[PDB]
Image (cartoon, rainbow over all chains, first blue to last red; front, side):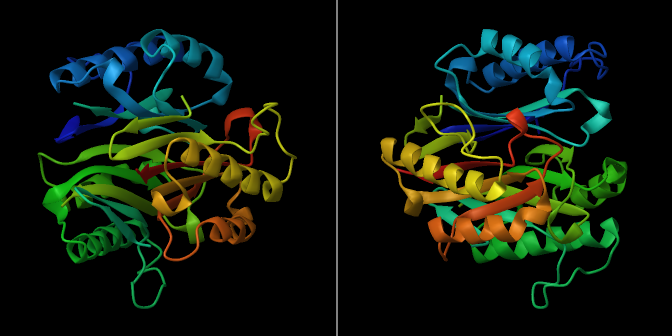
Length: 108
Length: 108
Length: 108
């Protein structure tokens, strides 16, 4: 599932920068994918009765930490200060060769 | 500890594909290790008063994402749809050169 | 934020081995950084009304799993048995080229 509610909380799967409907990446660029991830996350959270403001913890998995400034810039637009708790790191690879995956936990 | 209950929830340590008793890998193959991980997880969850059906979130750490189809096939047997929330990624290395590590969170 | 309380629980961001005040690494060595991470974590937890003994789950992200014995030794001093649930793995890279990042979840 994309999200599981256990009841004070909701647990999101790691989100990729895919057009939900089609399962293809929005583009090859981390800049588009990051924003698509965040958009996708907002949809999943809202459907779940959560929202960006109820997120308590995120984890950002990157293909390349050199992308961090662009990623942070975009992320900060959806999660302005004070923002969720967060961890960030560069992994060896992501599913479907994605540039970025973000998972999160939110309150209901 | 292998698991900590905080009380609506239980938090599992990342599980490796070891024969619990002996601490040696079941084999070198991701196919055996994945299944051993899942078996080990079921034991830990049950001992804890949880079970596969109460798992809400998993994280699969892989040595090689090329293993994903085999891993998914096995995983899907223990976690049929609708399955827990889940993240998957390839790490640089795992403890003891394991092929796969899975952690999870479950309800009580 | 460094930590978010949702209320039975507190979620910590991944902690690096920086002198909090200055934002520079305590040193280049994993041995100093690991200990600084743990110290930093204790401060964040206490400020939050938690403490090392209320931590339920940690995740250790390493630059090099060859560092595991030194890391484990230090960690075990702050988290003696029975210790939190825990996952450990080697990532491709960490923010600011850190040697180690640890995140955690604790009870209040």
